[PDB]
Amino acid sequence: PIVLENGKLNINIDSKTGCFSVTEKTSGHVWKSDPWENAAGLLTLTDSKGKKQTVNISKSKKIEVSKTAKNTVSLKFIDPVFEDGSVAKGVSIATELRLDPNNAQLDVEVTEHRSGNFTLYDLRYPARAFSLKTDEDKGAAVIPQKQGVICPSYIFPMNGGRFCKWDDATYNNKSQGSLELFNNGTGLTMPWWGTYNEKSAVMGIVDVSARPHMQYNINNNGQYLFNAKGVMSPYQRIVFLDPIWKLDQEKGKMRISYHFIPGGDYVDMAKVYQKEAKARGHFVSLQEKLKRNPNVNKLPGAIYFGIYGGYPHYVNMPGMAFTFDELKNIIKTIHDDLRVDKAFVHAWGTFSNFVPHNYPISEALGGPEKLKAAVDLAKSYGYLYSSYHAYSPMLENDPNFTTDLMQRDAEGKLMNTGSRWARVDPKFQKGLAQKNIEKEISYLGLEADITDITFAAYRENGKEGRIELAKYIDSFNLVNGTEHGQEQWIPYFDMFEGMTYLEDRPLSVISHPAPLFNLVYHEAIANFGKIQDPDNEVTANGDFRIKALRSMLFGRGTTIFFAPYEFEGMRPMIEMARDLVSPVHKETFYSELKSHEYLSADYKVQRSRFSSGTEVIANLGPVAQKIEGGISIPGYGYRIQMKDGSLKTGHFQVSLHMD
Amino acid sequence: PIVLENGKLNINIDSKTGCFSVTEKTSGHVWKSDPWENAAGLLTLTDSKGKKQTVNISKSKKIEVSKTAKNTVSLKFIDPVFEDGSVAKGVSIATELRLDPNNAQLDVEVTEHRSGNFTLYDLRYPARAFSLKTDEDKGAAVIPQKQGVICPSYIFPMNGGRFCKWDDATYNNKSQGSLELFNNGTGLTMPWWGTYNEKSAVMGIVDVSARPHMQYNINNNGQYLFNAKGVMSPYQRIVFLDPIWKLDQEKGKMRISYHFIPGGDYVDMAKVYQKEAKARGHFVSLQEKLKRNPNVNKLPGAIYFGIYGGYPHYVNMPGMAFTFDELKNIIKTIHDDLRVDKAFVHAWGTFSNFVPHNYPISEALGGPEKLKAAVDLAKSYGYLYSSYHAYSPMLENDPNFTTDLMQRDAEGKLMNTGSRWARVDPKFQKGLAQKNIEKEISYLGLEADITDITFAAYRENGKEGRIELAKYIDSFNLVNGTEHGQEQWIPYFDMFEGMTYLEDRPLSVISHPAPLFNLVYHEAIANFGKIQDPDNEVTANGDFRIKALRSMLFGRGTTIFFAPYEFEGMRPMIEMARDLVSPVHKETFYSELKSHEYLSADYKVQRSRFSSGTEVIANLGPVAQKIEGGISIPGYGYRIQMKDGSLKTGHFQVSLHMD
Ligand SMILES: O[C@@H]1[C@@H]2OC[C@H]1NC[C@@H]2O
Ligand SMILES: O[C@@H]1[C@@H]2OC[C@H]1NC[C@@H]2O
Ligand SMILES: [Cl-]
Ligand SMILES: [Cl-]
Ligand SMILES: [Cl-]
Ligand SMILES: [Cl-]
Ligand code: NA
Ligand code: NA
Ligand code: NA
Ligand code: NA
């Protein structure tokens, strides 16, 4: 066995298989290689017949493991063997393990692959590494899926219905699969993931040039590997997260940097990535944004109101569209009657053309002077205001629809025919914004802007055009927001609408929300709830009680998103957000979310500490539970220590009024 | 055209294509053939290269259409043509259209299929028939997906976040797909579906011997057919539901019976199927079940309580399992402190072996005498009691696990290796129940039983053994329940736990819950909420306010499902259920749900009328809304007219207590 060792880690590499273990010498915890098959890696490739197979590369005909520098071990896997015993002659995978001389850090890189006459597809490398043994390790996988989740490595008490779904999912396909980086759907928002137990933590950070996928296995014993053969899995239930290198498309450096943290958990992992986030240039603080634009200080304590008039989906839809006088009266009511001191008013439906032609201000809704009266009233309150804007859609029902501005692929076929909100090639979007946005800014005296869709993901195709648009919008120095966001866009915006949770998502029944993204970026980007899952709707992610409490724990702002006819029914939730969430949001807005903790065995009682001197404890479940010192937190209750020394305690109550 | 006609309907059959239209003569409404491609049917079959292709059978080389009896047209589609111009020589499809001589009913049957040297798979027939034109027809598709949904054929006002998801889904793949019959997952619980507009309704009833799937297309213009070619769809937005005959599997009679109802909607469709349900023998009334067993009258007004002790998933799990004295004290508190007058107590975790060995009563939990003490207390209150029982699982973590009782398929491979709760072959399950259930009935003096898993679906494979088990359980004449249920099991049980809604399901963002199953079967089977999604949990299906109101509209009972540590948090919901839902459940229990109506444009205000003389109006959204007569229903509010003429009005309020 070949050893790399420094003061902090011992890497033990098996010369027969290329598998390796990592001893974290402070805690003494040992991370084992693949517990199931002793596979260093899992390679998907075509056979002689053109059929895809997945093979254990530790079964290759020749495996060469040599110490090639003081702290580098080079590995080569030559001529893998298929299930029938034929050989993939001429195929090979070369990798390197590089131990930092001083730090508890191990770089792992796929340096070369050779396909011969076959075709190489997925490579899981390292395979089923850094795993947790279910119900032996008491820890979790840590996955930055949108705002982020943890997946405990053991079964624990919880509501009976939740428990049945949770345990069942660890025995079927719900607990295995893969996610991608930097999308606004099911995927990851930061290029890292990790595992920890009560002794030690490990996380891996993906090279900035690479786009592996992430395979997950959450307490599953691998029965999914055996269902087609109709036999029972012989393997043990474990938790692992693996990189999937897409050998058929990846042109970047296939490197992942593992960082080992004695006694660490998901908080420590997030703080390690926060250093890398700064080095990558993503981290531009809200304090720096405020120095550039004093109006950023209209955001702390603001409720984000989306008044949804059926636009962009329809122009002047009966029963949905608001007139500009109606918009003014909603703003007046929010301030004068509901006493909301700070607000971001976002009016969806102010133009008489379909996006991406964001003009003119609609005559049918009252015309420019009446919109200006509404915006002026909002400004007189100190509120931020934006219309709905988008430069990416090309909509079937728009009389101006054309395919002129849609992108085509190499075969001349239209792209995004299945995604109507993202059809305009980004290389045209700055020019579309230039058609009217300066006119609207000048006429309405705008202080703010929100732009939809374009910055919800960070994909390679079209990135240059998106950057051009972001730089143009940023050049106006408005308080500005965008849908969902990604870390790469943080330099250009003050707020993201979203970066919370999908309602239906892989892992939903076997994970707990954890504020991973905000543990990294709360000081750099403000976030609010998503308009599809706002704080006034009851969804898989909770009702108002749960969402208000989670908002304060995670450091996000309230979103109230409604059709005009619903407005009277929003009043009680606006008042509760005003009294409970808004003062905490205001106090914590610029601060670091220093720590988050789960304080109850069912993960429903949680404690967040912010560098404003604010501590938020809340109980997201129905039953009162005790914490340290015999302090009781009511069901749907909170205990919040403010910087001014006051202690806010209380809880939500549902009551039945029988007349 | 060939014409079949009676006093009610004119069937216009195109001799060149085999397509047909149906004129409903009293309204003048014409149901059209396929609006997109004029296809009588869509056949999937292999080509000469063995690759699957889907073809329009109206493009076949020879189409024969002739009147072969007074009210029968015979069609034959001979030698379909592939997209490359080659011919599926020797393939043919024979169908018949048979008009009832008197009634507005058309039978449509695939009578013969010949594959030659090709292989046949799906046949949609009739293809894209009985469609609704989006935003012109103001009606809905009607789909008995679990309890049931309707899908409106037009866009309407609703909450902004819901609206965005709804409208977007009609343009992407969320609005097209297929569902299967008689499962407990995403599929249908009755073998019918339909469409209606403001003039006319049509529904199709699938022959009892057949298992087609059902294709849906909910306001989609067919863009999914063109995405791979990268072109924009040239078709219009429509609603349709098609049978998919599985030619490779189906051995039954491939017949669907269309019933045409002037002025009808989903209520009239349900009442048509109710007559068929009675003719099929599924309908055994709760009044008849009460005559056989007077203890059935312990169900009306009963809350169903599941005390979830971590079993069957684990034996005596710390932090989840209750002792029998703890169980007794929960029952006592429910009666004495919470004043619950009727209840079904269901205790999950009474045995010290894993299911399917439902014995002995656990010594570690206090032993048989202590369980008998808790059951005796429940009986002294007039409550129903059952332990958790299951005869179908074979669990990995059971020391007694064996594959001996698992089923093997035609290849000799184990079945359900990925489905641990349904691994025992049904042909063994009566013998497993016989091992101890009569001992438990005798020792505890049981009046009730609930059996998990086995009756949640109605698949062909294993149905004989499931019927044998159902007959055996039924022979005890206990008040009895089972998980989820299907119509075919109604003769054997008094209640179903479930028959409501999955949390995550196809069509969720573009449909409204409708009580289709209970419009048929409320007089014959009682249902309660599902334990995974109980009324004390906040899910995609609502919080307690929404679920309590929907329960009264739909005629189901309350489910409170909790781990023991949660009990104190359940108290407010138990009290509200007791005050609001239980008296209405009690009054309506045995009655017919005669009608259900949506009374507001956003479908959130609804009115149900029961043959007890009870009327429930409720508002499942947040804003007060007015109905006929200017009567206002508050948000999360109700107006209930009881049998004796008294009026109950009220609403739920969420409030924030701040110390
Ligand atoms: O987890 C499930 C749950 O207990 C066993 C599983 N089968 C049906 C019950 O609802
Ligand atoms: O429906 C969507 C919604 O408005 C247009 C779509 N794009 C993003 C917004 O959240
Ligand atoms: Cl875009
Ligand atoms: Cl959140
Ligand atoms: Cl079964
Ligand atoms: Cl329901
Ligand atoms: Na999966
Ligand atoms: Na800005
Ligand atoms: Na679909
Ligand atoms: Na019975």
Image (cartoon, coloured by chain):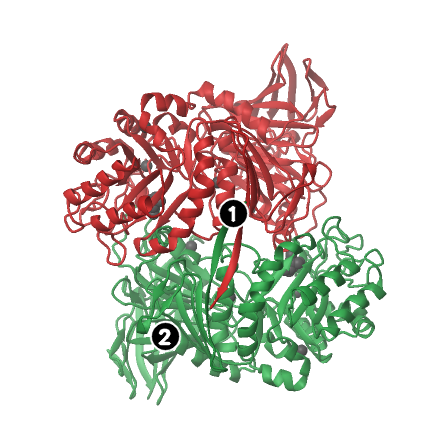
Chain colours: A green, B red
Judge from the rendering whether residue A610 lies leftward or rightward of residue B315; answer left or right: right
Rendering coords of residue B603 (x, y %): 62, 42
The part of the image, by quadrant, that contains residue A635 is bottom left
Residue type pointed to by label 1: Ile
Q: Check residue B546 in the rendering and tell me which mark sits there, or answer none.
A: 1
Please tell me the numbered disc located at residue B655.
none
Closer to the camera, B49 or A330? A330
Whether ligand 4 has any atom under 8 Å from the Cβ at mark 2 is answered as: no
Q: Nearer the viewer, residue A570 or A366?
A: A570
Q: Position of residue A275 (x, y in %)?
A: 47, 83
Residue A421 in view here: yes
Disc 2 on helix, strand or loop? loop
Q: Chain of mark 1?
A: B
Q: Which chain is mark 2 on?
A: A
Task: Please identify the quadrant where the N terminus of chain A is shown.
Answer: bottom left
The reply, left or right, for residue B373 in relation to residue B153 is left
For discs 2 and 1, the disc positioned in front in the rendered view: 1
Picture residue at 55% right of the left edge, 24% below the top: B271
User: Toward the viewer: B437 or B593?
Assistant: B593
- Please tell me the numbered disc located at residue A265: 2
Asked if one can make out residue B540 in the rendered structure from this viewpoint, the answer is no
